[PDB]
Length: 74
Image (cartoon, rainbow, N blue to C red; front, side):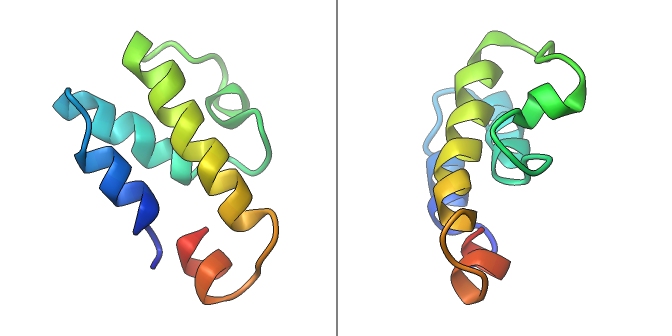
């Protein structure tokens, strides 16, 4: 599951673009500051909470495991 709970919340967005936003969120740079690590969340509004959210849930998916769940579920 390199993106199961995140590809699901991404696809269930009321905005095709929010999909990419959550895409990075799950692929967050490393810690909390996801797009923040990027440089400055400046790709859109739905992004801020879309990516931030997918990156936070992804944050808990990768902040506790380190295998199928982490390596994949992230």
